[PDB]
Image (cartoon, rainbow over all chains, first blue to last red; front, side, top):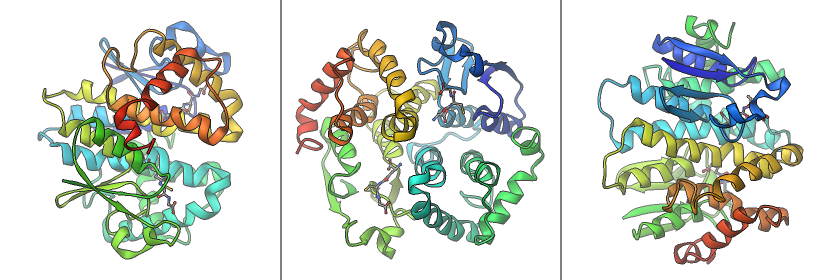
Length: 183
Length: 183
Ligand SMILES: N[C@@H](CCC(=O)N[C@@H](CS)C(=O)NCC(=O)O)C(=O)O
Ligand SMILES: N[C@@H](CCC(=O)N[C@@H](CS)C(=O)NCC(=O)O)C(=O)O
């Protein structure tokens, strides 16, 4: 089965949320970051940059939370996808991992970037329940996890963005979220 | 041909580098960021977050430099790839856009992150000429572009990382790099 390498209150929880959504079994392997386990040869053979999360699926190893989400989404897919359908999913995962996370969590750029990001998301989320339309997808795990960390880590709220606020509330109340990030 | 939306001294040059490596033509369209053209309705209809680069491939539009690189790499592949082969490339593109760029360019984390990132890259690059092995790939465009920007923006060098220094020197001398980032 999939082995997920993670640590307490790390991005491995985002992978656990998607595994809960997909109803897939997995082994959780704790990596003791406080004691430097991630900086030793055994973990560096899984991720040479010593970061969690990572997965092992047999002899295959993979790191970067965004690449793990895309991999799990592809493996679970029932209808074959083309380069354009994968590209739109990749776009949102890259956005969550760079443009969005940076604009919200980098103090030097937050005042300018955060309102613009949320204003753009408000327009999108006001027209459809999920980022890609009527159906929940891996994009909502990627983008939604970053947004859900705003109240948790910055003590900020989405009161000025009602569609964003309702979207994040809807994700937080999903049983799969409550069994992972929300636990 | 692909339309590439870019701006002076921006990440659109990374896409232009890869298009030149693939010997593909493209129609370059400047977006005047200094005059707020990226915040006007025509550009917001391409990228709702008002960032360059973006591409149009016929009626298909795509934003996030990393997603564009993955899309062009998929489109230019002659041998069909499975989820694991795509995942390894996705891993490096996410790394370049998050872990690597943040660890090098965010002042508050640079002291701890930068030597760790460079030491890991030094070990990989000391064993093979390119990140994935013997052959140059889209991963070298993604990672190499970020590393090439280190001397320019931070006034730092790779004197203590000789394989990183020789790898970057090699990339900067490539004709496709000179026709794009080096132009
Ligand atoms: N872009 C990476 C970031 C991973 C990351 O920063 N992981 C942290 C924990 S949340 C880590 O392993 N830190 C250990 C260290 O930097 O020494 C991803 O999304 O997977
Ligand atoms: N993660 C994005 C970042 C894109 C980005 O930051 N682009 C800048 C280039 S200057 C931009 O368009 N800035 C305009 C703005 O932020 O208003 C990518 O890699 O494409």
